[PDB]
Image: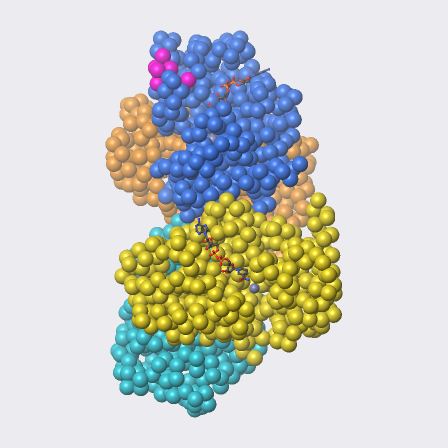
Chain colours: A orange, B blue, C cyan, D yellow
């Protein structure tokens, strides 16, 4: 069938690009509603206002309630209609960004996306994940296009807690493995077609970038400063991983992430931290070579991601919980079925326990 | 400076995808002006009308005058307002697509483009070239965004003259060398910033695809059939080179192309045919290793592109003509200035004569 | 523009060459003033006198006051005019040698240079660095030629404190990295032109020599004896590094050295010890691969050079001091601007902190 | 023994650098004798006079007799004292440069040389060959130093006959093999000591430059234009081979050259043309591996150098002539004695016949 690749229309990254926001956004619309993470507005709200004002734009700022829920979106629709804005800007982490995309779609207007962390591969995709106000999965909202514009201030990312950069590394490290599995199996992507070569190349670049640059990038995030390694890892966590997962494919790592959220123990760990264990689980399923397993385990360990179930607070009733994870992972319409030859609940259960054992031996040997 | 990559929002490629234009375009608008010339509407019109009709869309077919000019745009816009079209589809070669992009810009509506050939890398880009009704360059029209949707029917492309596929290879083969040069010089790209890693990776993938698949694809093109090699070369010629040139950078090869168009002798050659000589010229300028120049000359020769001035019909008064080419290639604003260290007219002159001598020696040996 | 390489007219190294000084110097002049480091004159003054006397030359010996200042040079001019000498010999470390060059230039006579340590790349260059008597930077004196003759007694070098050989390793280890950056950026060299191939080759040889021979050479310097590894490292620290920096180029490592001298904490560390940290800082800026960073950090550590700010006594108020270092490093006319794409004060600050972190982890891991 | 490298003080190369002779030479002297023959002053004189005039210098043009002989030197010195010149500029080919170096020596003043061809490696060296007014070898004049300044206008060199560039390649291609042999035998170099690492690295760079760039440069030479390949070959032919031979060492190839000049048949060939056969002779003597001899024969053949005795017009009485060559090459004082293990007349005789047979087989295969 057809080969399809999707992208945001334009992706921009640079130090202090928050000062140029207005100038980049001006071609899209004159009037703007900003949906902003509260923490971020706390240090940056004047800077944002000045950026728009200097470009001759009209802007109103709405603080974000914190969850991408139907209620929050509806609240923001009300504010948007009153403002009669021609476009939405999301500025924050993934929850803020998914909310802005959904809002913009319901208002039928352009959306710009300004990640203030590089924590997940949400920013670039044509998808918003909707939750209940209690923080539970509600539904996927499939958008007819990717954001018009994605603008990443690398200095703001560098000032955020380093754990959130690690989390994004854990999210993005899965990308190549999942897109390759889908290539091998011939699976349809979220873009609705088979893999392009472009998408697999970006997915592989993502993996190699993290291997070469991940540890260097963490030194910079820990000191809250911008270096070339950090710029490269931000691009990987954001553009490469975004295009790679959506237009290259999802498989076991994401299915296992979803499984793990059915366990209360891990629910407050970051998306990428759960994806990280999902990647190790996937390498058991696809029987990756010893040196590949070790390379991934070593990078994950070096940036502080979990490589064991105990690092996700899964310490008691492990067999029973892994049954739950395995069943959820193989539910109808999960992406585990994109693996070459598929995966049964028993195969995933087996992979979970064995990945945990590999993690546990890796750690012991590290003293 | 910021690092920027731009892309069409969605790129789709597949055999007989023209049957699916409706389902794919539906999410963007209900009412469409379809702009195509007589020849294309000749084979395509009834298929388009049925695909749109079955998706529940409205179409207004507007035969195209053949030239991308302000008058032609105004006329078509005339027709589009009357019909109350929400979106433009261009279907055909580069002049038709250029026109649909410009029209859609002036009317503030989305654009889809459906190339029926793969002969240049211009289609996916955020640029429209405006011409006189007589066919002379008027001005470049910079667009605020790349086409919303690009849809390539590989079966229609396979039916086009094989010469046009080779010409496309000639245009796309420059991509890597020009992006690499701009990366070495730190030049600004047409997307408005410095190179992303993503853009450089797609430019290099373009090059490697053409090396690996070029000759195989030309066998398919000459038999007018679709193979995976042809599919890959079409992607390289269209998506990879489009992103590579616009977000990776242009340099000497394109500037030499422009110089060659000041020479009446070379008027009957396609864009990519002149660019193919420009690439060899560039490799002399940057003093590429013998093995690289030989690889490029061999691929160019194997798919029928020119590697000498005589194969562009430049046979008489060659010194005098190359002074003209060199002076034009080095005109203020030209992309030759993106080469590391720049290039003077004298340097470009020298490279033109030596690239020609190199091509001549290469042809002599080949027999 | 023009490609230029500069050299001393003749470079000589050998064990006990101090005995052949007179014979080597005789073609330049009959009457000589020797400007001599006091420590050196303390053990070698009779040997020097005998060398000249045996060759039939006339010599007068002036002990060097210790700083290359305008006053010291003026004092020595007075002595030289009275002596009516036809040439100057400098014998000592870098401060003695720069003084002799400056003196010889002001008297308009030939200069010979006899390093008694291999501590910096001063000896061979067409430059004298002038200081205040208080030991502060005054001005660069650009000489119209390099020394006529450079004569290195490898046994005298071997008898000096081993720390001063390490210091020279730290000075010379920067050479390849800086000349390569300048090659990449197209920067002008101190010789006034673009890089020759000759200069880059000598710069690269310098780096590879230190990697292969640095540790072996330190064993010999510690035992105060001459081996082939020591002879090779002396040549690297003196001729290779001299030609390499002047005719290949300076970039971030030297700019960072200059920054660090604005900090009182490090002021009494040797030139090369500060350059060593500057090299690690540069490898952050140019995003060197992990294995290159590690190779350089390991060699620097093995010969006793600093790889952390604490090893230069920068232990308190580090952020504030690194702002100072970064601003000085990027001052107008510094060589940091020779890096590909340049470097802002923020980029250099970032590189300083991250290089320090890499150093600190390297040391921790070394237990 | 001491390790010594000698070099010209400053080497400058660039297109149209003749326009900058004044600014570059100013630092050495105010008043100049410019020595050039009719032909060179023919194209160069007005340019030189304007460059000097604009720098504020005085010039006295002294047309050169064509032969480097004691009479010619005395005459010119005559003119130089009258004019009260502080420095000599030689401009032209090797006989003019030789003369300027010798003159400047006898008058005790600095010398600048501006080669208008790149056909031998003699220009940069500290040696002048003196001849009879009739053109016969009189004596070698050893100079205490290399030229103060060497200035090569690559655009003038590109205008010279292509044959002279190839001849230069022939002269420079020996450099690495002769320096390597002297390094293996421990022979003393013309600079008066054992090999430095620097000199061996420049000799090997010369070889690799010619391999990589030789054929490319010959295309530029034949079109009479400047490319980077030509620039690199000019540097190899002039600076790298000059330092390589004088500070690296001469061996069999030069001795064979000398032997070949005792044979009237080879009189119409350039120095580098005879040396090219001498190199192949040397590779037989040292029993170089088949792949090395083939590489050298192929490069020599590709740029038009002789690889057989017939291509030096030695066609009759070849055994008898090769006895003469072998005896002369092995004369007391000749450099063949620097080969590891030495060489007897019989060994050299054998190598000459076998090198010829090798060349003949190589030409037969090539068609
Ligand atoms: N749509 C997709 O394709 C896709 C893909 C992956 C993940 N997601 C979604 O992404 C969400 C997770 O995003 P997230 O982990 O970024 O959560 P988030 O948006 O809640 O951000 C995490 C935390 O980071 C803080 N933060 C943000 N910027 C900061 C800054 N500059 N300095 C300091 N703190 C800062 C926020 O205040 C917040 O507390 C989930 O809802 C998940 O479903 C969507
Ligand atoms: N200087 C220039 O103007 C220049 C230079 C180089 C390339 N080009 C490009 O080349 C084009 C020139 O050709 P054109 O304008 O006449 O375009 P065109 O559309 O007429 O090109 C040939 C056509 O034949 C069609 N075709 C033939 N048999 C077919 C079959 N069996 N099934 C399906 N399709 C079939 C192809 O699909 C294609 O549309 C330009 O539009 C431009 O894109 C232009
Ligand atoms: N001109 C240039 O291109 C260039 C390049 C680099 C550095 N420099 C200059 O070099 C200077 C630093 O030179 P340095 O570090 O050699 O300083 P230095 O000349 O003061 O020598 C350092 C110490 O070594 C001692 N010493 C010298 N020879 C000895 C021996 N044989 N045995 C024992 N002790 C011996 C001296 O007495 C002195 O105390 C600075 O002024 C710097 O600006 C110039
Ligand atoms: N046995 C020998 O004497 C021997 C052997 C081998 C090589 N050589 C070398 O070759 C030389 C022989 O040639 P020559 O002495 O007649 O030297 P020459 O200077 O006349 O050589 C040719 C000249 O043509 C000039 N030229 C021609 N067209 C030009 C243009 N358009 N622009 C600029 N310059 C242009 C070149 O610059 C060059 O100076 C010797 O001087 C020596 O260096 C000598
Ligand atoms: Zn994810
Ligand atoms: Zn093009
Ligand atoms: Zn230094
Ligand atoms: Zn020679």
Q: Quadrant of the N terminus of chain A?
A: top right
Characterize the magenta stretch by its predominant secondary structure: helix
Residue C79 showing in the rendered view: no
Give the residues in magenta. Answer: B67-75
Nearest the viewer among A214 and C88 is C88
Residue at 71% in and 71% down: D345
Q: Residue, x 43% and y 36% (percent of image)?
A: B320
Give the quarter of the image for residue C350. bottom left
The x, y position of residue C3, in whole percent, is: 43, 56
Q: Quadrant of residue D80?
A: bottom left
Question: In the rendered image of this protein, does residue B155 appear above or below residue D237?
Answer: above
Q: Which one is in front, C211 or C364?
A: C211
Which sits in the foreground, D133 or C6? D133
The residue at the point 67 percent across, 33 percent down is A340
Q: Is residue D100 visible?
A: yes
User: Does B348 sit above or below residue A304?
Assistant: above
The spot of residue D366 in percent (x, y) is: 70, 47
């Amino acid at each position: 069938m057809d080969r399809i690749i999707q992208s945001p229309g334009k992706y921009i990254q640079g130090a202090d690009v928050i000062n140029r926001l207005g100038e980049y956004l001006k071609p899209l619309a004159e009037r703007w509603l900003v949906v902003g993470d509260k923490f971020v507005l706390g240090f940056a709200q004047s800077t944002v206002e000045k950026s728009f004002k200097d470009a001759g734009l009209v802007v109103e700022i709405a603080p974000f309630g914190g969850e991408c829920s139907q209620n929050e979106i509806d609240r923001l629709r009300g504010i948007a209609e009153t403002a009669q804005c021609g476009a939405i800007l999301g500025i924050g982490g993934g929850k803020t960004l998914d909310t802005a995309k959904a809002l913009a779609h319901f208002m039928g207007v352009p959306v710009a996306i300004a990640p203030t962390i590089a924590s997940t591969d949400a920013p670039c995709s044509a998808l918003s994940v909707i939750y209940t106000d209690e923080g539970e999965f509600d539904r996927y909202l499939l958008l007819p296009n990717n954001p018009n514009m994605v603008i990443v201030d690398t200095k703001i990312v560098a000032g955020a807690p380093a754990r959130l950069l690690a989390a994004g590394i854990g999210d993005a490290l899965a990308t190549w493995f999942e897109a390759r599995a889908c290539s091998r199996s011939g699976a349809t992507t979220m873009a609705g077609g088979k893999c392009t070569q472009a998408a697999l190349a970006l997915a592989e670049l993502c993996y190699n970038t993290l291997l070469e640059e991940g540890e260097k990038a963490m030194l910079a995030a820990e000191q809250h400063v911008v270096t070339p390694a950090l710029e490269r890892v931000i691009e990987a966590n954001t553009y490469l991983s975004g295009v790679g997962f959506e237009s290259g494919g999802l498989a076991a790592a994401h299915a296992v992430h979803n499984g793990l959220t059915a366990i209360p123990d891990a629910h407050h760990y970051y998306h990428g931290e759960k994806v990280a264990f999902g990647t190790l689980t996937q390498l058991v399923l696809e029987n990756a070579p010893v040196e590949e397993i070790e390379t991934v385990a070593a990078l994950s360990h070096a940036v502080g991601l979990p490589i064991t179930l105990a690092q996700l607070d899964i310490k008691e009733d492990v067999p029973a919980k892994m049954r739950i994870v395995a069943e959820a992972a193989c539910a109808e319409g999960e992406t585990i079925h994109n693996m070459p030859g598929g995966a049964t609940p028993d195969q995933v259960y087996a992979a979970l326990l064995v990945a945990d054992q590999y993690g546990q031996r890796f750690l012991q040997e590290w003293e």
